[PDB]
Amino acid sequence: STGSATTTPIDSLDDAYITPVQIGTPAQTLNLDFDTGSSDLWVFSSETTASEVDGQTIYTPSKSTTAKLLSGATWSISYGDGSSSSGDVYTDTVSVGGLTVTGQAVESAKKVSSSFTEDSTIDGLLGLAFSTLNTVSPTQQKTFFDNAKASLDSPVFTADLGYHAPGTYNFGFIDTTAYTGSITYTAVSTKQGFWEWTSTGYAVGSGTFKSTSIDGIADTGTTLLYLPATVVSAYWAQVSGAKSSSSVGGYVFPCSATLPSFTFGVGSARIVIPGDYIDFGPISTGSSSCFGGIQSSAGIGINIFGDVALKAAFVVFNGATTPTLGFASK
């Protein structure tokens, strides 16, 4: 089997991407944030605290003939940005782009943090990291990909995120028309439950490539590119007037700037992030200070190749017995 679904930016800045997902019978379609940095499939629901729902589409398990309470199971997750959600668990039929999993754990939110309430466009998350990170207790549950894998033509999924445009998540096949040149594969460590890999270095604009190992995660659920302070300083030093602002919470730059590109290494291959991908616009409406898309990972504890990086590439998440990651230009 295979599946193929379009993923769409939630706003003009590509702050996140949503992908329609069919849950239950008859189908209830919710727009979920596919997140290769976490491993829970959770949804706004008929059980979510009423005051914490503001415009989201909800899953109502009582209206699904295939829903079953997973008795005694609860979940609770806290994300790196400080957001969180928790609740109980149903199993139900879940389909993405024509690919169907029966008996998928659908984690129904009873509580969500303010950041989720305040974003009407995200109806929940669909985790695509390793199932060892799944938070369901007392019986840990599998991700949608883990459940689908044995049925797939090939045990892979691909992320093809657009810059200010829709893109595609494919399951079970590699679309050889979706990228240019060749795909370069690189080793993955699953020890922390992430798609963790080591970049071979970077360049800023037309500058020389610096060979240096940068361990980090491929994370579709994180907006920005978070890298070591040394690397980030070297980037922003090439932008007149750019500075790190403690009050804003990262590097800002004059909105009048033309940003340089940023290149990262994948083995001997190179992925170029155009400068425009690094512009996240005014810090507040009408401001001439703009927020940068490359930020320091210092104090996160891990480097994160988020959407800023991934949308410059066609990315293969290879879930073979020994997982790997592939990157191609596009």
Image (tube, rainbow, N blue to C red):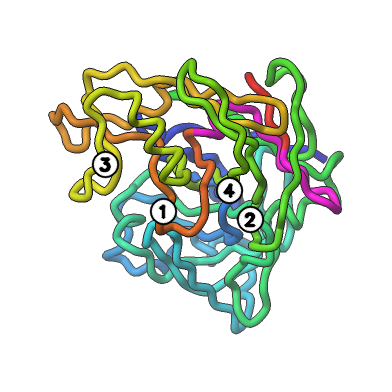
In this view, the residue in front, 326 or 221, is: 326
Assess disc 3: are there few (<14), some (14-19) or many (≥20) residues with their C-alpha within 10 Å of its C-alpha: some
The residue segment tinted magenta is: 309-325
Q: Is residue 129 visible?
A: yes
Residue at point 38% right, 51% down?
A: 56
Judging by the rendered image, the residue that carries numbered circle 1 is: 298
Tell me the tag on residue 194.
2
Judging by the rendered image, the residue that carries numbered circle 3 is: 244
Q: Nearer the viewer, mark 4 or mark 2?
A: 4
Asked whether residue 226 is drawn in magenta, I would say no
Judging by the rendered image, the residue that carries numbered circle 4 is: 216
Residue at point 65% right, 61% down?
A: 193
Assess disc 2: are there few (<14), some (14-19) or many (≥20) residues with their C-alpha within 10 Å of its C-alpha: many
Give SS at disc 2. Answer: loop
First reached walking from the N terminus: tag 3 or tag 2 = 2
Check contact, mark 3 vs mark 1: CB within 8 A.
no
Tell me the tag on residue 151.
none
Q: Nearer the viewer, mark 3 or mark 2?
A: 3
In this view, the residue in front, 117 or 46, is: 117
Q: Quadrant of the N terminus?
A: top right
First reached walking from the N terminus: tag 3 or tag 4 = 4
Compared to residue 82, the image places residue 292 above or below, namely: above
Q: Identity of the amino acid at label 4?
A: Gly
Compared to residue 149, the image places residue 243 above or below, namely: above
First reached walking from the N terminus: tag 3 or tag 1 = 3
